[PDB]
Image (cartoon, rainbow, N blue to C red):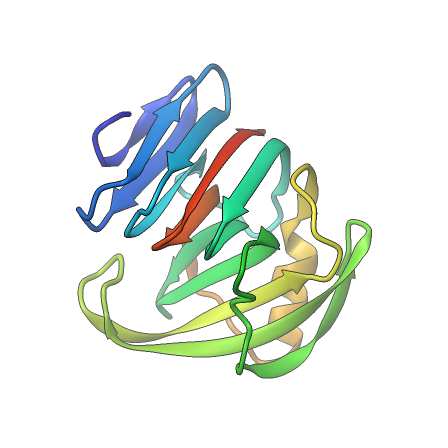
Length: 189
């Protein structure tokens, strides 16, 4: 494993964060590759991409994703002003992160319909400190662990629905886990 933090590896921004519980390891490989292995973890997020992201990036990902419990595989990032945490979810484990969330529409992109949702985090950690902020979700109906995400299709559909993004902060393909197990090996470009 590498130490939790952010930086650059083989030309790609990476972020790896965990809550200190144990049970997760993250490694950076050649090019845009990263791996994650976890067993009875706590909370974590790790992956590779860009800092800052853009609003018209076509992100390509490929590999394997084998969750055993609660985990997501997504294009994941933040905006500032307004502060937003966003996800384009290509696959997940035992929990669909949109469960119980208000549906804000649909968008068709890259071979599947996605359902769009907004949720809110109240006094939770963020890139600027503890804050209350919205989360935007596009959840792919047809699950996969390789493909291409035309981010503009999502960001445009979100804007159409009133879900405004500010200036982009980081933008990665990420494996997120919440007290689960699994393995993943993903290459980004």
